[PDB]
Image 1: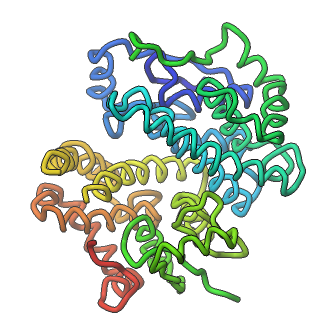
Image 2: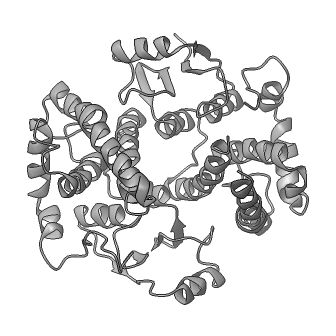
Image 3: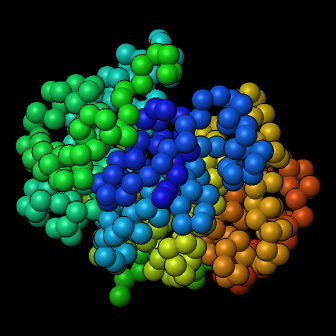
Length: 210
Length: 201
């Protein structure tokens, strides 16, 4: 059972929780509560770079979000079937991670910059990223982003749709195929269970958790 | 067949890691340099940039954007991405740490930021890779075989030297890796003048 080392928050660990849940993989989380508990991990040599996310899986102590995700995606066959399919997936999810990164860092923006930053996020959502993924879906007409089969690209994108909805439920309104992808993936058995109350899914980051 | 075409600007930027990787693999490539804001807009309106950005690389019938999608495909095609899923995890863990440090350096272009770059090099990143090389005592970071981790790290070793030549001095195995990799024939060519390798900006 994979053991997830982070703090009790979405942060850089949430996308891993989503991906494991969608693959129907149960995991334990060992929450950090203190600088004390983080230094315990560092001193015990558990963090190659002195950083979390860290995941204990299959004998390894994997740090770096993208090392974790790439490994979970291959293990459970959500990475496509060849390196040309992995290149489409990689191009998609790196666009997603670029937008996700902007959203993840909004609350820590300097207060005088937050209005512009959020404005920018919305402009790129509407003009850059959502048209890109809508055009992909319109291009093959299939139910999945790559290979007409479920992959990490669908999981990562739908996860981001939920965060855009939290920011502005109007932004997806002009994108019908993204809408239909959000509902179809949400109603996959493992994803629907993860979205239901009492799962490991984490809330938005309020102030005290901040 | 057609050799890959790199669409970027005439600078290191986010394309240099791809220049190093193709060259160390011994793959010849062309560069179509973006010289104006009008050149970027033509690539957009032609539909060549999924997210309207460069780096973009035309290879094997695709126009791949995002540095990491490009690198992942090239590393796999030319057998520089480990032999199994577990070796990939080690490589990925290593190279993403290198990316984190490379990212700070790439965006320096201050004294406050550079002072922090230097401290994290001496006490976080350089010890981490030295530990990996001491742990197994082999010539390459992963699997006792040249991999993209070695290429990406040694390229960064070069940029750290540009910033402060003393930062490597307490790390002998990083020094040795730098020498061995730089002496591989494809990398030694790429390091010689007149290669696509790009100067500091």
